[PDB]
Amino acid sequence: GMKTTEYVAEILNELHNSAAYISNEEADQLADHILSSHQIFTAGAGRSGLMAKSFAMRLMHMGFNAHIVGEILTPPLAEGDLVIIGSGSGETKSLIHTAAKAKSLHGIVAALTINPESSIGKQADLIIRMPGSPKDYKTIQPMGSLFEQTLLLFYDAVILKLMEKKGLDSETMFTHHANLE
Amino acid sequence: GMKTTEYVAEILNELHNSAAYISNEEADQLADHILSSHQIFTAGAGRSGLMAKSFAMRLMHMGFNAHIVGEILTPPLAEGDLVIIGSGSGETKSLIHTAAKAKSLHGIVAALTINPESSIGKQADLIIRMPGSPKDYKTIQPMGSLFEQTLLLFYDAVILKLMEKKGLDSETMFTHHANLE
Amino acid sequence: GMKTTEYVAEILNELHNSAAYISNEEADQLADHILSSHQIFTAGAGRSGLMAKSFAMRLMHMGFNAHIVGEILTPPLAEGDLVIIGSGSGETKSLIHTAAKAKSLHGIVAALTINPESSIGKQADLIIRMPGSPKDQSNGSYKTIQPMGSLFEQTLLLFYDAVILKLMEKKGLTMFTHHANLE
Amino acid sequence: GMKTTEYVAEILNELHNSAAYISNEEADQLADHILSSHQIFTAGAGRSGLMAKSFAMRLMHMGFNAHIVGEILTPPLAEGDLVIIGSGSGETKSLIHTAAKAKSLHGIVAALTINPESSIGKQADLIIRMPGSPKDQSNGSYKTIQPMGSLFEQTLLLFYDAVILKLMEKKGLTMFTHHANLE
């Protein structure tokens, strides 16, 4: 039984404990792939899909050629482009298909998933392993909320790293944002 | 009282009678604006919005720099870009705003609307007048169905005209379609 | 080569052919199913998907419990619910999945497609066959000057809007007070 | 300059500041309103809009009649319904419209914003003030190394997920059988 604001603290504490189990060799590699790929696609189902979109948007703001798998105006992938798949289970059929198709086209696949031996993980060129396996990790939140929150924060850290690599600062960064609404 | 297939014929007959009141000077101009603008944005609310998206998609397939107002990855408009607004009423507040903002940025606005003296029509550089004013036009369909259907067919005719101008044929046209699903 | 208004005429010309081809017997079953199923789900990919959204919207307007497969707020399907899938080829991988999954849940699947023997057509309880088969082509019948599946998508829209009319007929529905009022 | 995992730590550091700032009294009213209103509508633009969708999805999962302003299938708001608007600046033109329209329909409007005197904040029945005012800046309190409204959007997500917990507490809800099963 507790205050709404106290629940915010409990989440932040789950996030802090959980995020502090993510490995950095893989992450810094993801930034490097984003920097060298001509197009970047993000992907996810459900709420993870929302976090993908949030990451693609910020990538576009920074001037990258970023897209989201499954949207009306998604362009074709070409050889060497990157696909970033956020999936807790690593078993979502649609996402398994996206990874396979990417690979068939000689795209590069990065997967952020709990289980690296999952269907999606086994297709990936790069795996960023997220916490939450049967080994470890506490959460009082609904089914996949912690993973989804972790996805967002991790995406937004990759944004910071990209900013650093590009010598960009928050106060003065030019953003390519929509201007018709 | 009638067969489902008979209702299809009645719709086609409303469409045929209705579409045969559209003026061609304005239309051919829209194609010409699409051909010369570096970016094209489409826009609409509700079902008209769906037709906008359907038109933007086909524009992208043909290699144009096409976007839809209000989507996650919509880029900024620049001077000289085109905004194509489909609105029956010409009074939707959000669309009035999009037109005004476009104009402030020195974009070009084309409006497909029933009432050229509407809020959206008065902002437009180009008006394609659609049938259905108090003067004319029969429809046994729900509120805005005929206008929405007419929008689709008109968009798809502009596609044909663009194909013609570009010396493209349906059987052999290269399309830039999504390839990850 | 041709006025834009002349292309409209051509497009109309092609849709008239498509309408005469459609078997009303299957079409009429569709509306019956919409009227009896507690939930209705529409689906498609790309433009066909846009036409599925347009239909679901009008079903909602009529007071049906209508949904679109794949959206954030889509609820679970329960036994006896209807899923309506528009697919030209009947081979789109996501939609094969949706059809097979619906069937496994004992949903009723209605497929609108060119190929009744396609992967999606074979899962369907009801098939609404649209024109454009390699057969109707080589044998003189079907011709489109439009790209890709444009004629099919157009036919979908028009067919779905015709189904709305049949529904309104069957009911007493104007009473479109089910329209959004926010934003 | 810093490891990606070090940036995660920094982001967390900023969210902790934002949580201590939030007045629980207003937060608690939000959940009360969610529990009493027959329909709940969420809204936002851009990323904030994504967080509004994430919240609406979880409300649906809990069996609430939840909707997202601006979607194809969004139903009309009726008197007494709740609209929850996330906006940093409280000046986004569409959202000003949504708030004023909701109020005119006698909906209840809850605004989550940095500026309670913003256009949206002035329409709100309930305001959940988030940090980041020019004041909290110049006076030492608020600092972000992240672009644009990233910290605010993150705070929104986390705040909405906290509200879910309070709702689950208040109820007996696991019983997330309200999850999509098609596709």
Image (cartoon, coloured by chain):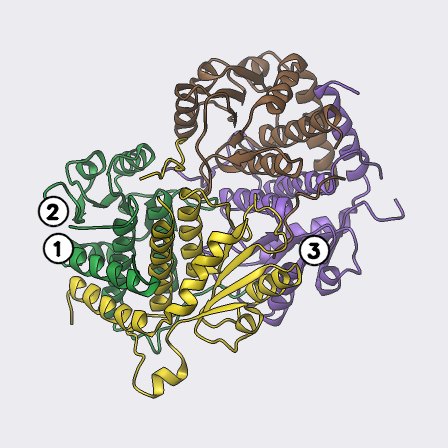
Chain colours: A green, B purple, C brown, D yellow
Number of the front mark, 3 or 1: 1
Q: Is residue B15 visible?
A: yes
Question: How far apart in space, not on screen, are marks 3 and 1 (Cα)?
Answer: 54 Å
Camera-side residue of A161 and B33: A161
Residue extending furthest right? B135
| Residue type at numbered disc 3 | Ala
Q: Which residue is mark 3?
A: B111
Q: Position of residue A112 (x, y in %)?
A: 22, 47
Same chain check for tags 3 and 1: no
Instruction: Establish if D105 lies above or below D119.
Output: above
Identify the amino acid type marked 1. Tyr
**Residue sitting at 30 percent across and 72 percent down?**
D20
- In which quadrant of the rendered view does residue B118 lie? bottom right
Vertical arrangement, residue D31 with respect to residue B130, above or below: below
The circle drawn on residue D110 is: none
Along the horizontal axis of the image, is A80 left or right of C151? left
Q: Which quadrant is the N terminus of chain B positioned in?
A: top right
Element under disc 3: strand
Q: Tell me residue C45's x, y (percent).
A: 48, 34
Q: Farthest residue toward the bottom? A: D139
Which residue matches tag 1? A21
C33 to the left or right of D148: right
Q: Secondary structure at mark 2?
A: loop
Using the numbered discs, state the Cα–Cα distance from disc 3 to disc 2 in whole angstroms. Answer: 58 Å
Q: Are marks 1 and 2 in contact (CB under 8 Å)?
A: yes
Three-letter residue code for mark 2: Asp
Q: Using residue D61 as the reference point, say whether residue A158 is left or right of it.
A: left
* Quadrant in the rendering for residue D124: bottom right
The residue wearing badge 2 is A136
- Write down the chain letter for disc 1: A
